[PDB]
Image (cartoon, rainbow over all chains, first blue to last red; front, side, top):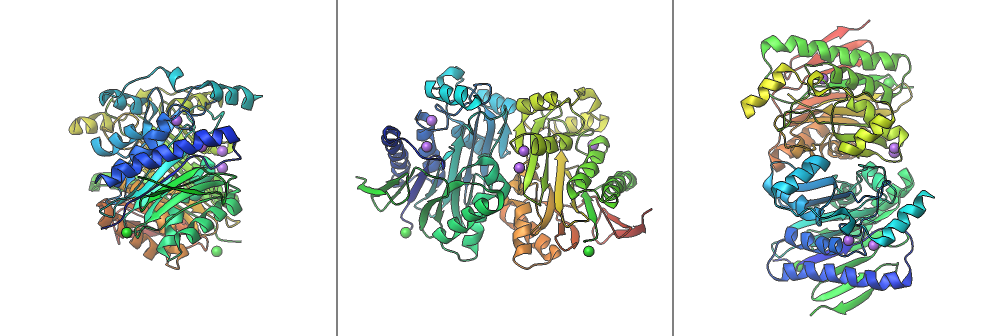
Length: 296
Length: 296
Ligand SMILES: [Cl-]
Ligand SMILES: [Cl-]
Ligand code: NA
Ligand code: NA
Ligand code: NA
Ligand code: NA
Ligand code: NA
């Protein structure tokens, strides 16, 4: 049976301040750690990635759940999806409000409906039906996000895993881009763009410019090259380069093959990432500055 | 410069009655003659796919715009998308209510906003700001879909085109599936699933069970096979073959390649379709049951 793996990412975007980096490092650590714990206790790939993403949702340092960037009217509107590599079963929500964990709502879409994707009003009704708390909107909104919205007027997080039965899955969640139009949905809830997971290939979650990732189908394009026998680093580079060269888009991705190989590559300035395997934890943000600590 | 071609499809769905076949043929042949007439003026592939789909939206026999199926709460919520293969520009909307023409609003999303995807209340706001008129739900609901729902308590339409300057496009529009949960979203506004266009390969629109179509990312998949060297037909066979085996889902698709080669194919029992090229209309509903006619 397979040695499990989890890989996590935050936003594939521009440079990050030094104080942030420390808060960021700990966040990538907490979610990688949380996800791997699940796998080391016999849990599924879906459990793991759901677990890591929740961690980043609950962490105000990340553009997902509490800490989501603001729309053009200063409200949080969140998108997410999750996908089971075994039968390709999937769950998604877009433009959901007043909840803590869009990724869990996403998981409920998959497991407790015959659908794959709900939006806005219906998503909110379904939440209520599932006994998902409704939190005051102001709780998701941070003071620092306000300064982004007030200023801008005048990145997506996620996870992939390979589990101890050799199954794969991705989860992704975002608040989107600062000053987005109300009801702007990006790449996250859109299968093949914000992520893709198939047991016959591997799994991918993307991040960066939502519209660009959508236009080129970045997650599934990444896996196609793996289908043709490109290596994981070979495929991520080709796929990302094509978003750059065709639609002028930048961003990042992480991947795990069904054989255990993994990578994190980004054409954006930075992308916080972490990978746990063989009892060790890998972490970074900027190119060629990784650390590798022991995960007891 | 290339010979222009438009292909249109109705819903990839169940047996059609002998009685009802003629009237679907009527609306389909109309849809195609609109698209083709736009192309003959040297209109763009994007113009041609939009007008073709506006005709099916307005026609109450087809499940998009007027004639949309009803959700669990008795109402019409609509999805649509359009894509320009020249630069991968796209627009899409989901869960929109009380407007005649979803496909027209997805194009406005492509052209007028920095985004490709608006949903529900955000889409209402944008449609208002652009002067789209509020249409009552009662003028979108057919007696058939008032009744059909009760049976529970048809399908997605599209077009692809290649214009007189080598540009390919797709457009697609739907009411979804009868008694769907409020705010359910199918493949139709998810780029790569409901359709995909790329001047460097071709354009596809899909129909059928939208959850399956999302899972397999059916439209991008067909283009993967084309790129790999397969004919439009083989590619259709392989992607629909895969969807059937892997997720036990049925549907169909139209595809036109960069070289002006085209096909309509389905694994459902029925898929109304019509194509116009070289002054000829080809149309059918059942397999190997095609007729050709001259066009004015
Ligand atoms: Cl292994
Ligand atoms: Cl030609
Ligand atoms: Na981040
Ligand atoms: Na967060
Ligand atoms: Na209609
Ligand atoms: Na665009
Ligand atoms: Na746009």
